[PDB]
Length: 153
Ligand SMILES: [N+]
Image (cartoon, rainbow, N blue to C red; front, side, top):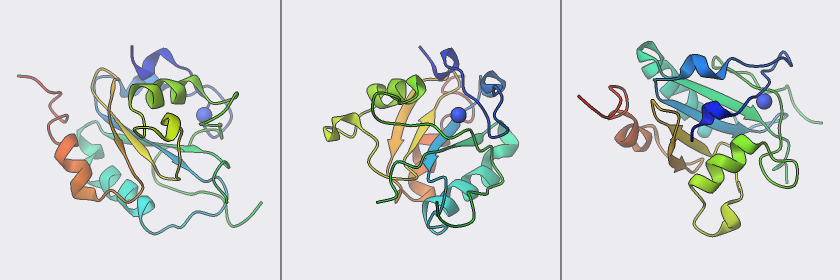
C-alpha cells in the first residue's frame, strides 16, 4: 500500500503524475486555498523543498478550505500545488484517508486538525511520519535525511 495507488488532480485541474515521485521521499501538506499565514509551515515547506529537491525530494500542497475558522491572494509556492480537496468528512480524498489512517493524531479521530500538517512519504510511497504545522526544519530532517538514500544499502 502506497500513495501511488491514488489518483489526484493538479492545480490546472487535470490528472497529476504522482508516480514521477516514486523511489524518492516526499512531503505532503494541506494548506488553505485562500489566506494562509505565510510565516511558519510555509517557510518550513519552502526551506525543505529548496534544501532537498536536488536529490529527488518534493513537496506537494493540497489546498483545502476546511480550516478557515473567499479571502486573500490565493496560495502561491515554488512546489506543486494540487486541486482543492477535502481532507476530512464524507468527501475526503482516499489519499488523505489512507495517510490519516496510517498515522493518526493519536485520537483527534485521526482527523486533520490544522493547516500545514504534513506527512512524510518514503521511497516506496508509504507514509512514515505525520508532522504538526509548527514542526521545525530540523525536526523534519531527523526523519527525512535517512530517506534520501532510501533506508538501505
Ligand atoms: N488534488
